[PDB]
Image (tube, rainbow, N blue to C red; front, side, top):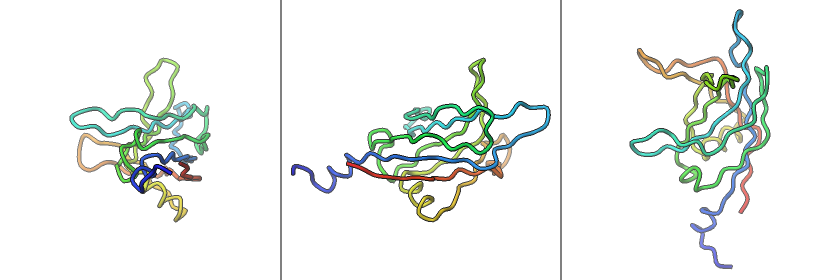
Length: 144
């Protein structure tokens, strides 16, 4: 064929099934309607959304349909991307449930180890707040 090792790396499409455990719920607050957004980090800018899941209504332990991520969407398999879980609101201002910063390589390791990553929230005092809720990688498949 016509593909070097680096060319094959550049052509890899990654299929990922994401799951969350124990999204927060408090009395007097409507249950979350969560979705995930995967965003590419860019110099001097706002992360660029490259993939989003469907919304799952009223679900604190969502499992979403697969997402497909290219190398062009993430930069490279080792490049960190942002993965944020948000609560979909009809008014269109979606509230942050939690953030993770992981590369595709890191998501594959969570899948292989059967381990989750705790969400966190960026704070206005001290370090990020680490939540009890977790993101898991139920499926991680590469194809050319």
